[PDB]
């Protein structure tokens, strides 16, 4: 057998919370290509549909970060410098959640 999918590389120089939403949201835009990698394996019916359905929940969850950008004006990088002990972990779970949503949905996608 063979395999050629799922890779993680490159990083940014900011708070682990900001790196987690930045990487998670940037990798969500990349994970939309992982739907195409998997479409060649599940290639039965929803091959061009489930790529768009998991893009539908991906782009909808991406929109939730747009609301967090307005929260960032209430919660500037002042308390977040110390809250990072739990906020950088909770946003680190957002990047990992974005992957175990759309990457794990990729491995959980069904054939029809």
Image (cartoon, rainbow, N blue to C red):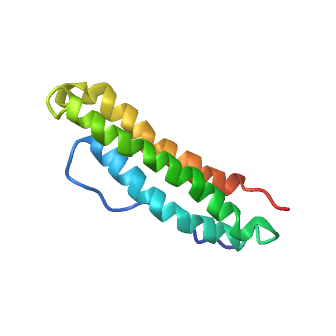
Give residue 83's quadrant in the image.
top left
Give residue 107's quadrant in the image.
bottom right
Q: Is residue 84 above or below residue 35?
A: above
Q: Nearer the viewer, residue 38 or 112?
A: 112
Q: Nearer the viewer, residue 91 or 45?
A: 45
Q: Is residue 56 above or below residue 65?
A: below
Q: Position of residue 75 (x, y in %)?
A: 22, 30
Q: Position of residue 111 (x, y in %)?
A: 82, 61
Q: Residue drawn at (77%, 72%), measured in percent from left and top?
A: 43
Is 8 left, or right, of 74 in this rendering? right
Is 19 left, or right, of 33 in this rendering? left
Is 11 left, or right, of 42 in this rendering? left
Q: Position of residue 31 (x, y in %)?
A: 52, 61
Q: Residue drawn at (17%, 31%), measured in percent from left and top?
A: 81
Can residue 106 be seen by looking at this rendering?
A: yes
Is 23 left, or right, of 53 in this rendering? left
Give residue 52's quadrant in the image.
bottom right
Quadrant housing the C terminus: bottom right
Q: Nearer the viewer, residue 74 or 26?
A: 74
Q: Residue drawn at (50%, 42%), measured in percent from left and top?
A: 97
Q: Position of residue 8 (x, y in %)?
A: 43, 60
Quadrant housing the N terminus: bottom right
Q: Residue furthest left?
A: 78
């Amino acid at each position: 057998k063979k395999d050629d999918f799922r890779n993680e590389f490159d990083h940014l120089l900011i708070e682990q919370a900001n790196h987690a939403i930045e990487k998670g949201e940037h990798q969500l835009l990349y994970l939309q290509h992982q739907l195409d990698e998997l479409n060649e394996n599940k290639s039965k019916e929803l091959q061009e549909k489930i790529i768009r359905e998991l893009d539908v929940v991906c782009a909808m969850i991406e929109g939730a970060q747009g609301a967090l950008e307005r929260e960032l004006k209430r919660t500037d990088l002042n308390i977040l410098e110390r809250f990072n002990y739990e906020e950088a972990q909770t946003l680190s779970k957002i990047l990992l959640k974005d992957l175990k949503e759309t990457e794990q949905k990729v491995k959980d996608i069904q054939t029809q």
